[PDB]
Image: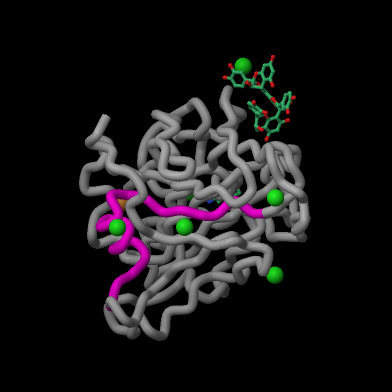
Amino acid sequence: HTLVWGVWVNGVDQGDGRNIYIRSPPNNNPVKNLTSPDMTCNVDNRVVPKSVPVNAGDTLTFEWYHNTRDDDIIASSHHGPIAVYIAPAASNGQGNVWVKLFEDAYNVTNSTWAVDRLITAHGQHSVVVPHVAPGDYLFRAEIIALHEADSLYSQNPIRGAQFYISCAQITINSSDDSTPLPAGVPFPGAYTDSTPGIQFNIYTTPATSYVAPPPSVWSGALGGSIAQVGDASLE
Ligand SMILES: Oc1cc(O)c2c(c1)O[C@@]1(c3ccc(O)c(O)c3)Oc3cc(O)c4c(c3[C@@H]2[C@H]1O)O[C@H](c1ccc(O)c(O)c1)[C@H](O)[C@H]4c1c(O)cc(O)c2c1O[C@H](c1ccc(O)c(O)c1)[C@H](O)C2
Ligand SMILES: *[C@@H]1O[C@H](CO)[C@@H](O)[C@H](O)[C@H]1NC(C)=O
Ligand SMILES: [Cl-]
Ligand SMILES: [Cl-]
Ligand SMILES: [Cl-]
Ligand SMILES: [Cl-]
Ligand SMILES: [Cl-]
Ligand SMILES: [Cl-]
Ligand SMILES: [Cu+2]
């Protein structure tokens, strides 16, 4: 159970974005239905009034929280991967449009899941803004909690993989457009009951065997990390 508070750009806090530049749902409940329209941008998918200005090559940092800003972020039980996708705003996140900019699942060296590192990072994870056409975009940040993912929602609606999905409205101003945005995948649609990483038993299967759901990260992606960029308590 987690939500996005706002974003940072190049380590500068853009301020509380809830219902402003984030398409915030009304609470931190997970999405579980893989075929639902709620998979696109969660349960209150509507245009919100602002779009955060960035440039190609900037660091865009999502900041998550549980109940209040810079709290425990998400329950430690919620082991799983983190991804970020992009789509053009005109698309309104419909069609084969979502392009993957980032994936982190399990880090064998530190023996940590993406979610564990997100807690340590005070809820912060980043992407580098790619050299796509200037204009308006949606960035879709997605946490998959696997603690009940030994079952499929479609078979048992009490259980399933849990999706914490947040869409940010981002405007890219300066960019030379040298890596024009390629075909992506639909949400809902890309994840099905047979997709690797959707049904998984984190209790019995080694984390080193986990494969995150496709698609792969776009070659045009410029980078990203789970790491604290800014200190929320210095406000
Ligand atoms: O006079 C305006 C001018 C606006 O641009 C807007 C206005 C009013 O109201 C708003 C709006 C939305 C929610 C609110 O609660 C509200 O009070 C006002 O509604 C919408 C609803 C929309 O569907 C879209 C809006 C807006 C914004 C947006 O601020 O703005 C876009 C826009 C307008 C003029 C531009 O020069 C431009 O580059 C982009 C698009 O027309 C349109 C839009 C979409 O068609 C599809 C989308 O996925 C999005 C959209 O806008 C959002 C947007 C929001 C603020 C911006 O500065 C901006 O550039 C774009 C965001 O890109 C998501
Ligand atoms: C899952 O979502 C689909 C598409 O909206 C809907 O038809 C189906 O009823 C949903 N399942 C449940 C259990 O609500
Ligand atoms: Cl659901
Ligand atoms: Cl309105
Ligand atoms: Cl960190
Ligand atoms: Cl550029
Ligand atoms: Cl690619
Ligand atoms: Cl980064
Ligand atoms: Cu939860």
Please say if 18 is above or below 157. Answer: above
Q: How is the image coloured?
A: one colour
| Residue 36 pos. (x, y %) | 58, 49
Please say if 34 is above or below 167. Answer: below
Can residue 161 be seen at all in this image of the molecule? yes
Q: Is residue 110 magenta?
A: no
- Is residue 192 shown left or right of residue 198? right
Residue at the image position 28 percent from the left and 76 percent from the top: 110
The residue lying toward the viewer, choosing from 60 and 161, is: 60
The residue lying toward the viewer, choosing from 194 and 75, is: 75
| Residue 221 pos. (x, y %) | 62, 62
Residue at the image position 50 percent from the left and 26 percent from the top: 20
| Residue 99 pos. (x, y %) | 66, 58
| Residue 70 pos. (x, y %) | 25, 41
Residue at the image position 72 percent from the left and 51 percent from the top: 132
Can residue 32 be seen at all in this image of the molecule? no
Q: In which quarter of the view is residue 47 placed?
A: top right
Q: Quadrant of the C terminus?
A: top left
Residue at the image position 64 percent from the left and 54 percent from the top: 130
The residue lying toward the viewer, choosing from 90 and 171, is: 171
The residue range painted magenta reads: 111-130
Q: Is residue 113 magenta?
A: yes
Please say if 159 is above or below 41. Answer: below
